[PDB]
Image (cartoon, grey):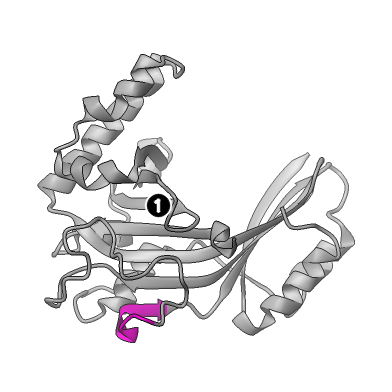
Amino acid sequence: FVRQTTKYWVHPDNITELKLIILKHLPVLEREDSAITSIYFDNENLDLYYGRLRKDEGAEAHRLRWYGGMSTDTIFVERKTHREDWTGEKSVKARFALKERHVNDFLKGKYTVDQVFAKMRKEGKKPMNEIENLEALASEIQYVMLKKKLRPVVRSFYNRTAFQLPGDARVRISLDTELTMVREDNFDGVDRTHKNWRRTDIGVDWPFKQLDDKDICRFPYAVLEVKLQTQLGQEPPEWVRELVGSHLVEPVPKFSKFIHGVATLLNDKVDSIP
């Protein structure tokens, strides 16, 4: 079989109609469970933003992500690294999990790499080479956090719903809704975070009505992702071809939420905008 993954933008007010159509064909796989929140880090010079915008060889993006509501304790510390084609290497994404109570301390170097990985080394369930890999990752994140004086700058939030028939991978779909960016920085003298890795005056309670609305960017689209596995040489189901060819959706290229968030919410601060 051949794979295809495609993303489409959807007008917000077509969401219900779109979900109804999908549900005729694929079933859905508290309301807070569907939340995905990521806190992107950068510094006062927006060094990481510019590095990612320009696609510098080696340009890193750093974000801390959690799935679900505010009782979720597992925080994923994530780093993306851009590699230019000329290197012969592919860009990479990597992450490791941390309990929430260790996040501030880890980022500050008060909770050490050895401490992060002590228990997983003790249980020896993970191959040591993988643990080594994760240690190099954690150390390098800790280092850039300090060296580049990074702090929380923008949050991305959205809800993800997935639709899938068990045992049939011909078509799998996800729908991301409530796409939102929220300021996390202190650049205007407003201390949004009070030394924490994320602001705590909101949770996953979109659309965050309690906040200063200038801190919020509500994205004007939802995102549909369709993944196909098509036996060569058959066709994808007719209903999918019809849907994707309809007025309800439009194909879109790769779009950075980090870049969109900074460029939109801190427009007065950037001197290059996509």
Q: Is residue 30 left or right of residue 199?
A: right
Magenta residue span: 210-217
Residue 139 versus residue 90: which sits nearer the camera? Answer: 139
Q: Residue at 35%, 65% (x, y): give it.
A: 155
Does residue 7 appear in this view? yes
Which corner quadrant of the image does residue 137 belong to? top left
| Residue for badge 1 | 65
* Position in image of residue 50 (x %, y %): 24, 62
Q: Quarter holding the C terminus?
A: bottom left
Q: Residue at 43%, 53% (x, y): give it.
A: 71
Classify mark 1: helix, strand or loop: strand
| Residue 35 position (above or below residue 19) | above
* Position in image of residue 244 (x %, y %): 75, 68
Q: Quarter holding the N terminus?
A: top right
Which corner quadrant of the image does residue 2 belong to? top right
* Position in image of residue 226 (x %, y %): 69, 58
Q: Residue at 30%, 77% (x, y): give it.
A: 265
Residue 66 versus residue 138: which sits nearer the camera? Answer: 66
| Residue 127 position (above or below residue 204) | above
Q: Residue at 46%, 78% (x, y): give it.
A: 207
